[PDB]
Length: 153
Image 1 (cartoon, rainbow, N blue to C red):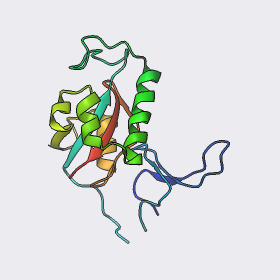
Image 2 (tube, rainbow, N blue to C red; image 1 turned 45 degrees about the vertical axis):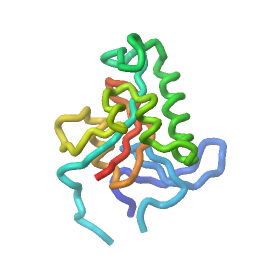
Image 3 (cartoon, one colour; image 1 turned 90 degrees about the horizontal axis):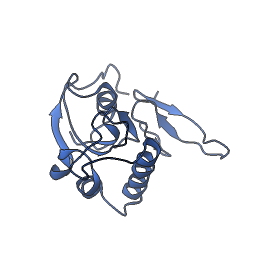
Image 4 (cartoon, one colour; image 1 turned 180 degrees about the vertical axis):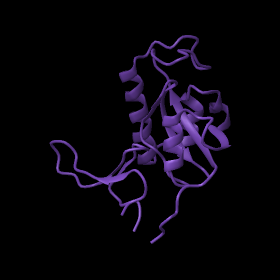
């Protein structure tokens, strides 16, 4: 029971019963599913993401600032914060991706078009293919920094 990645947990020092995904890093009270077996995975998936980079990113630069100084932890604070804002409904994913993303895709609502396994960084890819149409991920790390993936197709 539970699609690839999913699991049942309980937050530290806080009695919370919810679902967690080891691949997407998504957290939610609601159960992801409710009999669709041998479902495997699609061959292609269109995705949008918002990327925050830190000092250890392969390319500590982006269209937002000539030189990235923020640390890993600081960049993670930002992701979380953007996630908090997305989920609360206070701010949609696209506008946040267009305002703060460190990938040139920011000028495209953060879209990346449909892709298949092979091109993207394995961490980002595994997440993307583990996400379902309309689902959003939790923090995702790659040599580019920390992402927030949103599968559109």
